Structures are given as structure tokens and as C-alpha cells.
Amino acid sequence: DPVYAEAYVHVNQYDIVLDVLVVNQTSDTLQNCTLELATLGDLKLVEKPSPLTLAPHDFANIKANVKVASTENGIIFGNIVYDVSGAASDRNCVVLSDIHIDIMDYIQPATCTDAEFRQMWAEFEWENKVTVNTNMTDLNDYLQHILKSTNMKCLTPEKALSGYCGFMAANLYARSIFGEDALANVSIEKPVHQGPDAAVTGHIRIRAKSQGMALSLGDKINLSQKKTSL
Amino acid sequence: QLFCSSPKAALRYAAVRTLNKVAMKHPSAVTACNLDLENLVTDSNRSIATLAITTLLKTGSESSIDRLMKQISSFMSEISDEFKVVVVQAISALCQKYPRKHAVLMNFLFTMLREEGGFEYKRAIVDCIISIIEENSESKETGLSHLCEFIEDCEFTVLATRILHLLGQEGPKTNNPSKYIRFIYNRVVLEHEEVRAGAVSALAKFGAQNEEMLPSILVLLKRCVMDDDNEVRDRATFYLNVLEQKQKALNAGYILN
Amino acid sequence: TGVQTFRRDHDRFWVLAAHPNLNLFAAGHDGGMIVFKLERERPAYAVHGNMLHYVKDRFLRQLDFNSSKDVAVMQLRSGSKFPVFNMSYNPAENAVLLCTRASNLENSTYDLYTIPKDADSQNPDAPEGKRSSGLTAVWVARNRFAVLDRMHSLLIKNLKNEITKKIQVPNCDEIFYAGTGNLLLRDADSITLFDVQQKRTLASVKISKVKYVIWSADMSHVALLAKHAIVICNRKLDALCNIHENIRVKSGAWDESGVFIYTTSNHIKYAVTTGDHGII
Amino acid sequence: LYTVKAILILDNDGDRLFAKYYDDTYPSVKEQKAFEKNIFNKTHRTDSEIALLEGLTVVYKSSIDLYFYVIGSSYENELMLMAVLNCLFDSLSQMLRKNVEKRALLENMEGLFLAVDEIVDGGVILESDPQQVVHRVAL
């Protein structure tokens, strides 16, 4: 419509913030509908610019701050239905459920003593694993990339050698914003001429408390793993 | 047969196992399906449970039906007259008709085995592994692939002991080095001085033989991977020290034998 | 007439309904309820100047241009309507070829119609109207050979013209019995190129389809559909870029060979031009 | 045929208040209990239509109060074998006018005993039907 509203999400530092362009290229501060607040996850949405005019030929920035540490809603991965309403110069609108709400980001790296670790590794919520196998790179650059992407930790090296092969299994740990600790041992082949690694066939073993997020994390990482057309 | 075919003589079960022998002749076999289907279906009567395994076995089966059964089994096996024991017997038979052979089945089975599980597979494993060796199975790459992976996340240290020992001998006659290494590292990965230890011991037959790339590197590796933890330190040191002590070529010859 | 009876529990009901939105259809019962959703997931097309033709997955026409909320394109080029096996433009800004009675039979009817005015069956007299019998008609690679099914199996259809309706049993070659593909892919997972008989492959290339190959209007589009994902090529396999998204529903568009339009919310966007990217 | 390893009438508390190893070649009161344990614990009042343990026939029964064990070899058909087992419940029941109970068991053993020797004697079943007995006995 003249009124075209375009919007995307910007998550700028904790705060997932809503860029909205409602552009009302309308022929007037056309009447506007209705909007509703809610508890969200460890967030709650929390602002609406008050008016409801769709000012003529006019462009507007409508900001929604979201509250990023509260409102539990357990509708995982978000993907929760959201409403913009048809309630005034509007007969309809958008009701939307979100998608676009993923993990790789959330968790931060976190750390451990290795013996205890091992013991723990085994000990943890075993229940998820996903496989590493396939890419576009060596796990040097590739590993770094993935690491940065998820913002997460590989705890320690043994020099055995991530180079000549290595035939290295890398142990990774991370802790998030709402505090889950997640453990990995992924054991991986690694690039190098007619030696081995341009796939893996390494297994990524994922432990996160619910299997459902945990595996999903293994996936998420799987998405993360490579670089291709989303 | 028919007359018995529902526990008149709950006797009927035993017979199929041998007493009245079956391994069929070709049209003859097709005819057999119905009777086995009754037992297979009924799922009850200790006499029944046993019967199901022998009849099905003797007469043999299509792949497809197995599938239906795998689910059936999924519930059944735990106790359903205490199915597990008949089943272990059944299983022992399974390992035999396919002891790492129809590997696709072996894997399907493997997935399933682990899966349907309980725990009770382990016992079975003792047999299964043995079967695979008996063939001296050759879709190992795959077979092994399943084993390796699953076992990892199918646990039990005890299994590892056995398999280790076997593996210990086998090495580079079956190649696929990077993978195999890849595995091996993992096996060690686990704690236990003890768990760790096996990868080195298996290795001696292996190392000595070397494979599609190994001698140079074989020499490089023991260096690259090294450990403290005292007696664990010692294990690294000692193997080394032992290594230290003989011309590694000689070293290999004496020790290996 | 009683077609058939369908059984799926509930020995106790009192309502049935079909939407007056017609969106969905549903049946109500004591023990409970079911809703089922319809689609001819993915469904056939033709192009004539500044106009789109669709054949419904679900939903009627929507065969170009619009005016208020949603408009299913009702025209003399009835698209999403008929009982389609296959629809292909017979290029002209004035022609289409259409198979109806769809389905599996021995063979169906195709009545091929004129954009100037389609019909129940258009004129066999007219060659922008012709109808005959035949089960399906299908494109195949190296672009002028075609498949026609005019037996309930492999007839090859080959014509220089794409006002085409040609019948060719030679190239009989089963080892794939009548089913679905369109540059040959009875789930070949390849688009495989041929002439009008041969018992020796010219060649197959390993690439894949929506089970349709997208031509830039008529019959030469190296812009490719894939069922989920679609790939952009220039004519034939040259994988220019490869598209993927993950919503198992929508579309993105080419103007001609590889002009990439992507839809982006309440924003509609050019994925790319020259070295450019843009929101029109 | 010198075929009874033992016939035991067992409590279902794994106890045995009767055992006669008609025939035996393994021992220990303990091992007997142990052997007992594996199987009894396992069958736990539950029995089976048939059970084979050891390639050996186990015909065992349960009552409404008591667990009956016979151990024999799967090397001698059910129908007969059971028939003796059947004979055991039934006669005791009729004659006494009452079948086995824990109570019954507790008041007096002897009758069981009396019967038992008569029916079977070692690994050879001298008999398996009541009637003969019934007349024969008159205690």
C-alpha cells in the first residue's frame, strides 16, 4: 500500500529491537489499528510508539524495544505468534509467528579442568549429537569461523597437531545468557593433501539438557558449519 | 503342526529348532509362512515366544516383514514372557545367520539392537562381535563404522576390552587409515588410563605393520601424543622408554610376539 | 452417485462442513474431529505478454494482474481450473497446450486452446485449438524434443514448433514406466538429453528440477526450479549461483534468464543486477 | 526313568518345604537354594505353560498358595510329564477334599510325603493317576 511498512529486526546489544518502517505513504495519518503487549521469553516486549495515524505520504520509525532478560514464554526458538492488527484503517494486518530466532549467537564460550571435564563430559546430558562431515575449508579457518559464529569455546589443545593432520578431538564448552552450559566433543579428520580432511566424518556430540534444544543446537551448528544460500 | 499350532503341545517350539529340523527346499518354504505368522502374531506363551524365534529363523524371512517385527519387538522383548532370554538365543542365531554379513542387515540390526536395547544387547554383543570375526567380515568399513560410532554412545567399558583385544591384532590389513586413526583417538579420548591404554596396545601390531601412509608418521605420532598423570605419565614414558630401549624395528618384532 | 465410502472411525457424528471461505474442509464427530488441506503441490503454467498463468496447487486462477485484496485470474486462458496433467505455453501471446482429464488413464484428452478464446475443447480444425487424446506432454532436454505420452507410456514428442502435439512411440524405452519428469527425471535426479527413438544415451547431466526446468518464457530457461531450492543457471548447466531459502511454500522470480527477484516481506526485492541489488 | 532331579514343593518365598532329589548328582543345600534362586526368583510365582531350563525340562506349577517344581529333562514329553504334575494336584485335592495351601502345608507334611513316595520313587515314575492310589491308600 502507499503505506508500506517494511521492517526488520536489529538486535543490537541484548536488545532485540524492532526497526519498523511504517511508511505511510498513505494519503493521510490513516487510522491505525491495534497492537498488544506480552510477556515474552527471557525478554518481554515492551514498547510501542503510541499514535495511530498513518500520516500522509510520510515515513515513520517505529521502534520496539523488547526487554531482553525477561518474560518467560517457553515457546521455543521463539516462533510465537505476534500481532499487528487490522483494527483501524486496516481491515487486516499481519499476524505473524516468528521464525528467525536462533541459538548460535546466544551462548558464550565457557571453560573447565580437563580430567574433571572428561568425567563430566561423560556425565552430562548425553542425549544429542550431530555429525560433522563436509564443508569448503580447513578446520583451521573453518573452525575459527564456526567458533566466532557461535561465540563459543573449545577448551584446550594438545599439540598433536591440527596441521600434519591432526587426528585431534576438540573439546568445546560454552555458557549462555540464560545460563545453560553445553558440552562437546567432536572428533574430526582435518584437511591436508593426500592425508586426511575435506569432509570430516567427525561426530559432533552435543550435550544440552533438553534433547530438543540440544540436538537442535547440533543442527544449528550444522547450519553454522558451512557457508551457503540460506 | 496346525493341530499343535496353538499350545496343544507347547512342545512344538523345541522341535523347530532342530528336532524337527528346517532349512527348507524352495517352493516348500513359501508354504511355511502362515504358521509362523500365527506365533509371530500371538506373541504369547513362553512356549510361543521361543517358537516365534525358531520358526521364523528356520523358515527364514523377507527383509520387509522384519521391519514390522522390529517395532513389535520393540515393545516385546523386555518382558513379554521374559522375551529377552529367548531373544538372546534368537539373537545368537541372528549373529550367526548374519554375523557382520548381510551387513546392511547387520547395521539395520545394529541400529536397532542398540536402540531397542534396554541394556541387554551387551551380552548379545559378546556373541555378535564374535560372529563378525568368524566371517572375518569385510564391510568392516561400514560395520566398524556403526560399531565405533554407536559404541561411542552405547557405552560399556567392558565391551571395549574385548573388542580392543581383537582390534589389537587386526589393524593395517584392513586399511582406511585416517578413519581408523580418527577412531582411535576417540577411543582414547575417554578417560581412564585404562581406556586410553588400549589404543596404544592395539597399535603395536598395527604400527609394526604400518599402512597406506604409516611408518614415518608412525614414528612422528607417539611424539605428538604424549601424557603425564604419573602412572598414566609412566605409561606414555614407558612405552616410549620401552621404545627407547629397542631399535624400533626389532622392538616391534619381539614385543608383537 | 455413491462414489465410495470412506472409513476412519467415529461411529457417531453430526456435522460435516466445507468452508464458505472454502479454505479448508473438515468433518466433525463425537469421538472427535479432522481437518485436511488440499494442494497440487506445485502446479502448471504458460506466459503471454505481461501475464502469468498458474494452475492451482490449491486455489483458482491468479493468472495475472490484480486490483484490491486477492484476484484469481479468470480469463479465456483458464489456468488454475481444469483437470490438469500438464500445461505448457505454446508460445504466441495467443496459444496454450493443455491436457485434461489429468490423471492416470490409458490416455486423457488434451484440448489445446487459443488465448484469443479458449474452449471446452478448441477446434481440431484450428491448430491453436486442436485436441486429441494423449495422457501427458513433457519437455525434454536439448530443447525441441519432447515427450508425449500417447499410450500410457513413452511416446516422444518432437517438433521444431512448440505448437506441438506430436506423437512418437519410438523411444519407447521404459525401465521407468509411465510417471513424472520434464527434462527427463522419473526422479532421474538428472536432466537427460535425447532425440526421437535412440537406445543409447546422448547424455545426462547431474543437476535436478522442481520436476520442471524454467525457461526464460518459452522453452529456453537456464533458470532452474528445484522443488525446495531452485538453482540459477544460464541456459543449461552453468551453475551461476544456487538458491535456497527454507520455507517450503513460496517463489522468487525471473525476468527472463536469471533476473533474480526475490520477495522480501512487505518489501519485494531484486536480489541482484550488473553488480547491483535493489528494492524496487 | 530315574529321571527326577528333584521334585520340590516350594514355597514361593523361594523356600522349599519339600524336596526330594530323586536323582541328584549336584549338591549343597546352598547350591540347591542358589539354583533355586535363579530360577525361582525369576519365575516368581509366575510359571510358564512350558519351561525348559537347561535343555532340561522344568515343569513347574504354582497353585493358589504353593509352587511346584519338578525338574526333569527336555528329553521326555510334556504331556505325560505334566500328567504326573496334574496327578499331584488333583488327587491331593480330592482325597484330602482339599488341594494344597500354605496352611495345609503347615498343619502336616506327612500326607504329601506318603503320596510322593508312592507315586514316584526316584528317577522312575512308578505311577501318575490317582485312583489306584486312592484305593490303595487308606490312611
Image: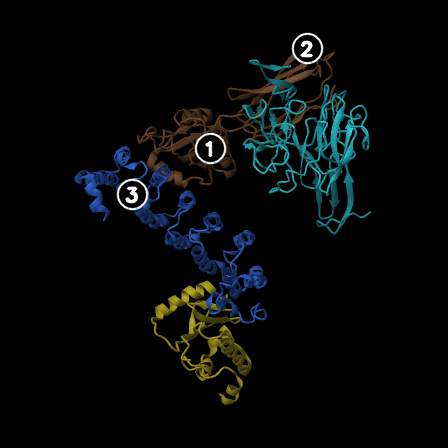
Chain colours: A brown, B blue, C cyan, D yellow
Viewer-proximal residue among D99 and B47: B47
Q: Position of residue C186 (x, y in %)?
A: 61, 38
Task: Give the residue at mark 3.
Answer: B206
Q: CA distance from mark 1 to mark 3?
A: 42 Å
Viewer-proximal residue among B204 and D90: B204
Mark 3–mark 2 contact, CB under 8 Å? no
Secondary structure of residue under mark 1: loop
Task: Give the residue at mark 1.
Answer: A180
Q: Position of residue C56 (x, y in %)?
A: 72, 31
Q: CA distance from mark 1 to mark 2?
A: 45 Å
Q: Which mark is residue B81?
A: none
Residue at 76%, 32% in the rendered image:
C81
Looking at the image, residue B31 lies above or below residue A113: below
Mark 1–mark 3 contact, CB under 8 Å? no
Q: Residues within 10 Å of mark 2 (few under 14, many from 20)?
A: some
Name which residue type carries label 3: Phe
Task: Give the residue at mark 2.
Answer: A58
Image quadrant for the C terminus of chain C? top right
